[PDB]
Amino acid sequence: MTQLTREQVLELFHQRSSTRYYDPTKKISDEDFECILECGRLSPSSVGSEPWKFLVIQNKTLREKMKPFSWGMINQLDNCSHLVVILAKKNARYDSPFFVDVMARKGLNAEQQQAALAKYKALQEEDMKLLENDRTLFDWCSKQTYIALANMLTGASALGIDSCPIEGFHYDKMNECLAEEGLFDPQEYAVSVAATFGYRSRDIAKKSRKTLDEVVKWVG
Amino acid sequence: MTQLTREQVLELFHQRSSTRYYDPTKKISDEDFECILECGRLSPSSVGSEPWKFLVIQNKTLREKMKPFSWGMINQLDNCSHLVVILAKKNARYDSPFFVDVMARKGLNAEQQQAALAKYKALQEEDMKLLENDRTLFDWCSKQTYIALANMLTGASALGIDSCPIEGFHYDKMNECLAEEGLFDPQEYAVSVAATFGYRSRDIAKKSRKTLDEVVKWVG
Ligand SMILES: Cc1cc2nc3c(=O)[nH]c(=O)nc-3n(C[C@H](O)[C@H](O)[C@H](O)COP(=O)(O)O)c2cc1C
Ligand SMILES: Cc1cc2nc3c(=O)[nH]c(=O)nc-3n(C[C@H](O)[C@H](O)[C@H](O)COP(=O)(O)O)c2cc1C
């Protein structure tokens, strides 16, 4: 098993910073980048839903086409080693074909599936109130994809690989772009969040966070 | 700098599983659990919004009060060492006082603030269409808190401490419950997600995930 001291764990999450300036001469090995993607694939997700898809956008022409509506990463698109656009599943209702696969991956038998479907329905409809509209239910999947996002960042960091998480683009324009390019079915998926990966070309900014006393309330 | 091999990074995310059964005779040390909290505090977040608050629910009475509407952690409420209920910030509009503190942590002068506010309005109103209603704006904050959740699960795993993310509870009753105890302002925050921590009483269940070829689309 992988074990670290508190000092090592602190440094790992302290050393990961948002890299906005990448060295264009350095690329991540195929072995290293596969490892990053694995951090995403292995991430936990609510009821094992795994509602993500990781588009890896290495095509230079597609990257260029995104610049005019991707201000959050416009200078990173040229220089980063790798770009992942994470999609989230649309309409992941408890009764959709999508949850049939969720349960098959669990090896549920028919009676367990009936209980699981009741669980999912309760969670979605009553506990979490996700079935109000398409957007709330999509955002539930999206939340899960940010878990994958976070583990990919941390995993990149552990490998000595710099990253930047990315929201700064027009989402309608991004969805239209990528869907028009044939990269996903827009009725089935939509863009959730993005992230660049590479090796920094400039200095990383000092961490700036709220204090621990500001963000924690102990209820003893 | 903390550095891991590819194999160690994989094992970090294979060894972490959702712990349903905690040994009640085993407690996380105060130092270890502060380290876990630091993983969440140091997490990245969109425009550095850090829109989380971490409620550490150690009180036994209060844990017991939560049991009847928290089916997703019924046995865990009793046996786990530590419980965190993560809140996300409500109504985190670009022009809110919440964002006055966001810019202040970034040391922005007056000119930098008017540019940042213009960037925040663009992101919320046009790019991400977060201002449709209160819930879409909340769910944006909630997505950031799932990064902090992920990093606390991962940091715990590197310390050798087991965890389980928790959505399985009635959100309306839990909001009502924690607010009634006077633990947060329901008009400023709402419950996002929860997580248990401690030491597992059973061996790790093998991962079941979609394959890498199923979740990755390479666009060369
Ligand atoms: C956001 C979220 C909420 C979850 N809620 C619960 C819960 O309430 N009860 C539970 O036992 N597991 C919960 N889990 C754990 C998942 O069921 C689990 O991650 C999935 O089945 C994969 O198993 P693994 O994490 O052990 O690989 C949740 C996971 C996530 C990411
Ligand atoms: C979901 C999300 C989206 C982000 N989008 C952007 C982006 O579009 N452009 C950018 O340069 N930074 C982006 N960031 C990075 C944050 O601005 C950054 O994490 C924070 O301001 C500074 O902290 P750090 O360097 O400690 O990560 C984003 C971060 C997250 C979590």
Image: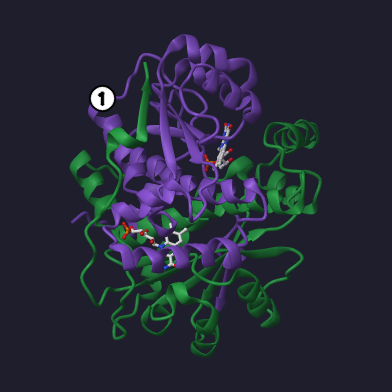
Chain colours: A green, B purple
Left or right: where A208 falls relative to A70:
left
User: As rendered, which of A87 and B76 lies closer to the eye?
Assistant: A87
Residue extending farthest to the front is: B110
Q: Residue at x 36, y 39 (%)?
A: B157
Mark 1 chain = B
SS category of the residue bearing label 1 = helix
Image quadrant in which the N terminus of chain B is located = bottom left
**Number of residues whose C-alpha sits closer than 10 Å to that of mark 1, classed few (under 14), some (14–19) or many (20 or more):** few
**Image position of A127 with respect to A107: above or below:** above
Asked whether B185 or A81 is in front, the reply is B185
Horizontal side of residue A19 vs B174, given as left or right: left
On the image, the x and y values in percent for residue B153 come to 41, 40
Task: Tell whether circle 1 marks a residue whose Cβ is less than 8 angstroms from ligand 2.
Answer: no
Q: Residue at x 52, y 63 (%)?
A: B121
Q: Mark 1 points at which residue?
A: B30
Q: Name which residue lies at 39% across and 81% down.
A: A75
Residue placed furthest toward the top:
B61
Q: Which quadrant of the view contains residue A95?
A: top right
Residue with the most extreme bottom position:
A61
Residue at screen point 64% across, 20% down: B69
